[PDB]
Amino acid sequence: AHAFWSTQPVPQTEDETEKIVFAGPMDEPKTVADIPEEPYPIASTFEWWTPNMEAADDIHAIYELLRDNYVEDDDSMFRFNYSEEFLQWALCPPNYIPDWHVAVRRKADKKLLAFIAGVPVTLRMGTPKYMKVKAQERGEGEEAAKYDEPRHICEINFLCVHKQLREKRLAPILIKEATRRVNRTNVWQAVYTAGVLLPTPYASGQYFHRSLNPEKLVEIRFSGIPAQYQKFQNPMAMLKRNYQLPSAPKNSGLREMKPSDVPQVRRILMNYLDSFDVGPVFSDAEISHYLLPRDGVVFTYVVENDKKVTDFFSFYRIPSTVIGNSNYNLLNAAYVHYYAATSIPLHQLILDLLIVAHSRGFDVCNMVEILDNRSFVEQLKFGAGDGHLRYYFYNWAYPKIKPSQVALVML
Ligand SMILES: CCCCCCCCCCCCCC(=O)SCCNC(=O)CCNC(=O)[C@H](O)C(C)(C)COP(=O)(O)OP(=O)(O)OC[C@H]1O[C@@H](n2cnc3c(N)ncnc32)[C@H](O)[C@@H]1OP(=O)(O)O
Image 1 (cartoon, helix red, strand yellow):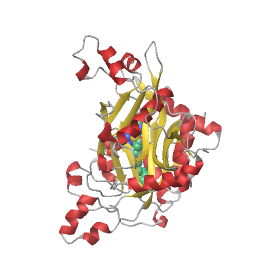
Image 2: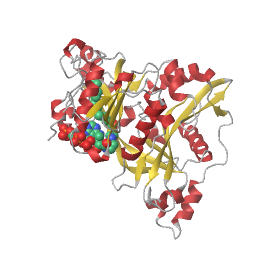
Image 3: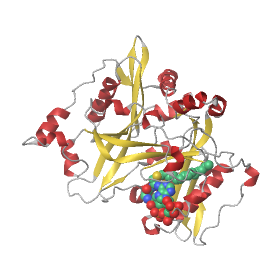
Image 4: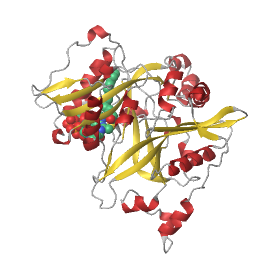
């Protein structure tokens, strides 16, 4: 029973989603004038707050909320510790809408108690290729193509309720108020991800992890000894030896991305992402924002061949707090971001990502099996994680697809 989600324009069961064969909206069309102009009522001791993401004080307040209260593993050993610089990056892409960043604070002391953030994204989200095949074989190509134009929608992230206020139905009102503010902008769909099962994902991908410092990872109980290494008398030693990375990048033309690479990176990324059912459309401004290197936040490298950029990869940094370990209190994790390989095998491109991440002191490289990420798991010695990242739409019926048809990276 979902007292909240059963009232919302989402598919309500896996059985329902299994039957969806076209993309399209779920709610009746509405207009902005149908949407209340007043923020939803909230307890008189709390207030809605829209942070100013240019104010160091406001960014710091969000930072501290998430540091102490955002996603935790089930054993409370690790918690994400997004940096202030990362939050300003993730929350403030080009043309972002300040009113889509929704917070609740306590009036008396102005303490931040809850947060949810929406940013604009332009998403291809029309009927998937294989369902269009089946639709065309039914003479319904027209209906299957109705919504192929990229849509300007909302990407939701960073939903967080302070630990002391959990299970008091604050998340539904936060979500409802964000929806109100987005709808008041004439935007009617959103996309979000979660590591938990909600009604009802259109895609789910397993997490995979590449140890860069396997001794540390075993000590902090992030990962175990892979089953294939349990046959050894000293598995950690063999792990270190087989996981040892080349001292140097295998691609001699590798260098950090620079502003003049933006147009070529845009073109090769968009050409690659076009082959996926669900994916973002990025302008030069958005390519610049999301991919140009930013210290401690995002790292992007290009390969030149024949004087031109032919390949690139990116990763971003999310440290996690390690709780209860007497030897370590932080885990430095690199997350595979966007990439495109036009002249070298993808596993050779991503090997250079691992080499660079190791040289920069990261402990582990994490990814979800979206894009073509599954294809280099075995080759580059990634191990399967316990987690799955689920992909969801708000007010968009969508057929179930494999994660290999998803090209939207979530931060
Ligand atoms: C058109 C524009 C639309 C824009 C909006 C689109 C939708 C966006 C949707 C949000 C996308 C977020 C994407 C991310 O950021 S996913 C990461 C979410 N954050 C965390 O896990 C951080 C740590 N946990 C917390 O802060 C709290 O436990 C949260 C805030 C998660 C729940 O707070 P609390 O534990 O105090 O519970 P409650 O009593 O207030 O509320 C219980 C209700 O909340 C439903 N619930 C539980 N977990 C989630 C979840 N992860 N997404 C959506 N709904 C969730 C649950 O099914 C129940 O509804 P129902 O089962 O009774 O019906």
